[PDB]
Structures are given as structure tokens and as C-alpha cells.
Image (spheres, grey):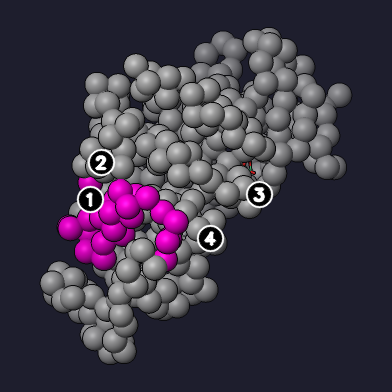
């Protein structure tokens, strides 16, 4: 498949904050 | 009315339906299915271990560890299906969360951005930190053992070869991810080498040490790292292969920038510390998380630890497969009505 942005990942979302 | 997949009975219904073949694996076929009770899609591994002691061993360990483990980056076991009596049980069906693919499959079709490489690496180490806190060694880490979603969520799977770490005390198609000391000399260091190898594979889309056999595997590792400095020699216990290494012609270290010319400098530096020949000098899991390559994702407050160590004191490779079948029947009983 094709990878979405890293920001689609929930754990990654907790990183951006 | 048991459902069939490629001329193979999958008896998972009525709860699980709409079976679709995913792939083949050790002793068993995996399918996606729909769970009609919880209204969710799952993966189901059909396992038929009972004719082989070794297979029984891997099944029990896997079930025991995955049921004890709770982590975001480690696959869980949702349910286990088997016959209501032990004489009737010829198969065990393991239900897990359905993941879209695995890293091995992904790397065949696709080149990875250094962004995705970095984030994938963080999850591997984050899962591994938990594993090592329980004082468990995975021992099989490789790309096919890393499950993925298009949302870039990663989970570690296949704990069949896992065991409690001890200093100190069976195949496995590939030696590609196995630490040099395994060929020579167990220890947490051997999982780090594996992760080092996986990182290298995400970089070039190829395995770094694709040896064809025992000594060829060594020659591959040595073709990259060069001949050991000693201190590596003489940190070796078995003296039969020290002298074997001494009997080997000299090899030059290939600088990590000549290989992987398109790779992050921070990544290469961390790669270097996972791939060190000496296990004692090799970087630990929590240090690796703290490496500047991972600074973006590094958060020790959100990187959970096991509540206590995992316990296998039980007999490892010795037990008769009939007994193992009894143990597997007992371990899966909590998924049965009337337990
Ligand atoms: N939870 C899952 N979700 C989606 N696919 C899975 C899942 N678990 C395993 N698979 C797939 O099933 C196939 C076989 O892997 P597996 O079932 O773990 O057998 P194996 O020999 O135990 N593990 P492996 O050494 O990686 O092949 C692979 O194509 C995997 O991608």
C-alpha cells in the first residue's frame, strides 16, 4: 500500500504536541 | 458449515466470517475476517502445531507472551478458537487486530522517505523497550515480524522464538538478522543487532548481511565491519571460534557513508552503535531511544515499561509434545465458555 503522512498516526500526534 | 480457504478448512464461525487469505507463515495460514460480534476486521492465524514438539513450543510461548504483554507497538491476541475437548483439538485459531501489511512486504513495493524510516525506527525501539523491561528477548526481529498500517502504526509480532534473558544457557530460515556472537558464543544485545539490520534494510531496501550459511554469514558481517580490532577478539569466550576469526584473512571496514550514501547522518551514527561487533559496546534500548536521530519522537514519559518481569521458569525444549498440547489447551481455556 501507500503510506499516509506520519501525522495520521496517533502516537505521532502526541509527539507534535 | 465450516468455511474453506484455498481448500483449507478455517473453522472460525459463526462469529468470524468473510475470510480472505493473507499469507503463509510458520505452520499456518493467516486470513483477514470480519468479527460479527464486535463489528470489526481481524486477522486470524490458523495454527496446527501438534505433530511437532518444536511447533508446540513456539505456539505456547507465543500465546503466553502476547497474552501477558500489553503495548501499543506489540500485537495483541484478541481471541483464541479451539475444539471444546483436547482429543478434538487439531488446530488453534489466533485472532488478532488486522494490520494492513508488514515491513518486509512494504519494502518490496516501496522506497521509504527518511521521515517514515525515522518514525518506524522509533516504534520498533519503543516496543522493544517494553519487551526488554519484562526481561524478554524477542530473538526473531526482522521486517516480516513488523506489522504496519497505512497510518504508519507499527506493531511487533511473532514471539515464538522469544525467551527470558539469561547470561547464559531451531531454525529460522534466515541468519541475516542474527548477531555475530550467536555464531560465536542469551542477551538483550542480540535484539539490538536485529534492529540495526532492519534499519539498514529500510535505507537501501535490501538486507545488509544476506549470508547463505553459517560462515558466509560471518564473512558478510565482516565484509562491512572489517576484521575485529581484538578487544572483540579476546572478549570472546569460545576459543575455537576466536582462532577461526584469527585464521580469517584481513577485511577492511566499509564506512557507513559509502553504503547508504542517501542516509541521514544521525541515522548512520545510530546504525553504527547498533551494529557494533562487540555486544558489550553495543547500544542499549533506552540509549537508542535517546539518540539525536530520535529526538523528534523521544518521550520517556510516554514510553511505557512492563509492570514486572515475565516468567518462563518452565521447561523449554525438553517437554513432550503431548504435554505441550495439554499446556496449550489450558492456556487457551480462558477464551472458552464455562471457564
Ligand atoms: N495481525 C496481522 N494482520 C495482518 N497480517 C498479518 C498479521 N499477522 C500476520 N500477518 C501476515 O501473515 C503472514 C504470515 O506471517 P505469520 O502469520 O506471523 O507467520 P510466521 O512464519 O509466524 N511469521 P513470519 O516469520 O513473519 O512469516 C504474513 O504475510 C503476515 O503479513
Q: Is residue B334 left or right of residue B21?
A: left
Q: Is residue A7 left or right of residue B183?
A: right
Subunit under mark 3: B
The Cα atoms of the two marked residues, 4 and 2, are separated by 25 Å
Would you call the spot at circle 3 few (<14 residues within 10 Å), some (14-19), or many (20 or more)?
A: few
Q: Are marks 4 and 3 in contact (CB under 8 Å)?
A: no
The Cα atoms of the two marked residues, 1 and 3, are separated by 31 Å
Q: Earlier in the sequence, mark 4 or mark 3?
A: 3
Q: Earlier in the sequence, mark 1 or mark 4?
A: 4
Q: Which residue is label 1 attached to?
A: B283
Quadrant of residue B120 in the image?
A: top left
What are the residue bounds of the magenta stretch? B259-286
User: Residue at the spot x=36%, y=54% of the render?
Assistant: B196
Badges 2 and 1, same chain: yes
Badges 1 and 4, same chain: yes
Foreground residue among B311 and B288: B288
Asked whether mark 2 and ligand 1 are closer than 8 Å, the reply comes as: no
Residue B167 visible (yes or no): yes
Q: Which mark is residue B292?
A: 2
Dividing the image into four quarters, tell me where ligand 1 lies: top right
Badges 1 and 3, same chain: yes
Q: Nearer the viewer, mark 4 or mark 2?
A: 2
Q: Which residue is label 3 attached to?
A: B109
Quadrant of residue B228 in the image?
A: bottom left
User: Residue at the spot x=58%, y=30% of the render?
Assistant: A4
User: Residue at the spot x=44%, y=52% of the render?
Assistant: B198
Q: Which residue is label 4 attached to?
A: B206
On screen, residue B281 above or below B117: below
Would you call the spot at circle 1 few (<14 residues within 10 Å), some (14-19), or many (20 or more)?
A: many
The Cα atoms of the two marked residues, 2 and 1, are separated by 13 Å
Amino acid at each position: 500500500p501507500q503510506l499516509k503522512p506520519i501525522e495520521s498516526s496517533i502516537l505521532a500526534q502526541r509527539r507534535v504536541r | 458449515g465450516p468455511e474453506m480457504v484455498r481448500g483449507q478448512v478455517f473453522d472460525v464461525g459463526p462469529r468470524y466470517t468473510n475470510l480472505s487469505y493473507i499469507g503463509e507463515g510458520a505452520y499456518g495460514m493467516v486470513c483477514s475476517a470480519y468479527d460479527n460480534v464486535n463489528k470489526v476486521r481481524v486477522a486470524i492465524k490458523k495454527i496446527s502445531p501438534f505433530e511437532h514438539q518444536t511447533y508446540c513450543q513456539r505456539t505456547l510461548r507465543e500465546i503466553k507472551i502476547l497474552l501477558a504483554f500489553r503495548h501499543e507497538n506489540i500485537i495483541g491476541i484478541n481471541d483464541i478458537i479451539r475444539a471444546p475437548t483436547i482429543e478434538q483439538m487439531k488446530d488453534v485459531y489466533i485472532v488478532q487486530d488486522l494490520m494492513e501489511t508488514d515491513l518486509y512486504k512494504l519494502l518490496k513495493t516501496q522506497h521509504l522517505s527518511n521521515d517514515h524510516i525515522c518514525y518506524f525506527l522509533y516504534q520498533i525501539l519503543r516496543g522493544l523497550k517494553y519487551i526488554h523491561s519484562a526481561n524478554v528477548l524477542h530473538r526473531d526481529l526482522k521486517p516480516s515480524n513488523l506489522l504496519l498500517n497505512t497510518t504508519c502504526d507499527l506493531k511487533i509480532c511473532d514471539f515464538g522464538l522469544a525467551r527470558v534473558a539469561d547470561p547464559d544457557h531451531e531454525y529460522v530460515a534466515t541468519r541475516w538478522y542474527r548477531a555475530p556472537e550467536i555464531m560465536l558464543n542469551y542477551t538483550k544485545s542480540i535484539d539490538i543487532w536485529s534492529v540495526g539490520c532492519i534499519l539498514a534494510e529500510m535505507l537501501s531496501n535490501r538486507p545488509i548481511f544476506p549470508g547463505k550459511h553459517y560462515l558466509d554469514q560471518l564473512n558478510h558481517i565482516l565484509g562491512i565491519l572489517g576484521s575485529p580490532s581484538q578487544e572483540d577478539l579476546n572478549c570472546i569466550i569460545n576459543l575455537k571460534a576466536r582462532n577461526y576469526l584469527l585464521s580469517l584473512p584481513h577485511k577492511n571496514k566499509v564506512p557507513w557513508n559509502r553504503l547508504f550514501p542517501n542516509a541521514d547522518s544521525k541515522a548512520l551514527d545510530l546504525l553504527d552503535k547498533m551494529l557494533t561487533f562487540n555486544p558489550h559496546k553495543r547500544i542499549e534500548v533506552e540509549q537508542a531511544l535517546a539518540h539525536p536521530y530520535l529526538a523528534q519522537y523521544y518521550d520517556p514519559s510516554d514510553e511505557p515499561i512492563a509492570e514486572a518481569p515475565f516468567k518462563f521458569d518452565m521447561e523449554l525444549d525438553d517437554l513432550p509434545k503431548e504435554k505441550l498440547k495439554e499446556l496449550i489447551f489450558e492456556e487457551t481455556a480462558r477464551f472458552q465458555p464455562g471457564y
